[PDB]
Image 1 (cartoon, rainbow over the protein chains, first blue to last red):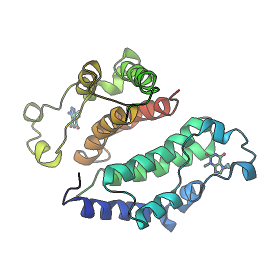
Image 2 (cartoon, rainbow over the protein chains, first blue to last red):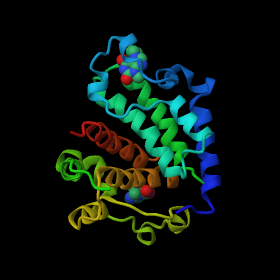
Image 3 (spheres, helix red, strand yellow):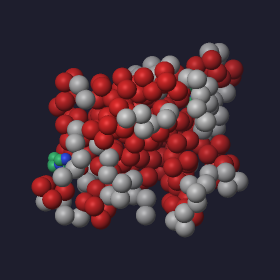
Length: 114
Length: 114
Ligand SMILES: CCCn1cnc2c1c(=O)[nH]c(=O)n2C
Ligand SMILES: CCCn1cnc2c1c(=O)[nH]c(=O)n2C
């Protein structure tokens, strides 16, 4: 059920999303900007291992289209994106190091939810 | 709606929870074993800042009582526990360093969901 705080909480989520896409974090956010193109990257097992792909452009479209009804739904998608990276790649891969840094940006600001 | 995979996914979640409570991680998991006793710790603003307290003993009771119906519900509570730590404490506090390490244990194993 919708709560009167959901619009303002979704604004905070949109602020976080804007930050994740901003130049400040681009050195480690770039692998998450668009859907993984498994074929182009030679990752021919990606869709056998990752059942629910997610990326920041998809989160942005869902925010713009008012798909997310509350902050928890938004956060589950952002976390799904990171989890897919931790599931598919070896833990010492540079893409995992980038994911951990971007997730730290996300989690610390999500925790500041007004 | 319940899925036939929910029991096995909840078993994986229970395995993670057991690991988080195990001696292997006790050096950094201990602040999360029981509900924050704000009065005992002198944290007299804790319940003004943290609207939804969560801790591993509460997660365990909810698992034992079949409160969680799926893995996503379990994961939201574990993540809520970490988020409360990131929201209340300064980011350089030792309890935050412990939270980050325990959350890394959680997220990497949650990502291995069968
Ligand atoms: C930097 C390696 C190519 N690459 C780009 N994006 C990626 C990857 C990858 O190997 N694994 C991933 O999960 N993603 C998101
Ligand atoms: C180690 C400091 C006391 N202490 C114990 N548990 C805590 C804290 C704290 O200051 N902040 C917390 O969030 N928790 C979970």
